[PDB]
Length: 50
Length: 50
Length: 61
Length: 16
Image: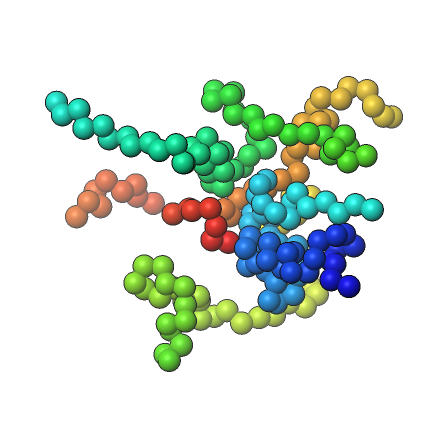
């Protein structure tokens, strides 16, 4: 019961990546502003599958 | 006059990758500039993910 | 604490955000400064290239 | 002092 985003990523790792890249996570998750999320940023390349 | 080499390059830095990330950071990356042969590699998302 | 120290310091001047910053947004009349940029299978190329246009697209870098 | 020239009318890898 430690997964997120309907994928294999744990809440810990997702939280750490989002905090490291967008300063997001201590005040609720949400899609970061586009200008903060460049081509090599985290969220853009995240792709859950099932 | 003085052959005091002003470029001290190590083999630990990855200057190529550094410039790759800088070009993404400061400006848009999608657009193509022919002069520097500036055209970032990319796959078709309907091929990477079916 | 002057409450000041606690701020990212960017240069000997503690960086503190604008005073008039608290906030309201309800329905009509108010909107933000960063915005929405936004047969079959024949030609192909212009299309691959456009899919690639889904990244940062304007400014306010 | 140099106003006669003016027209008249840091990034490290992270930092959010």
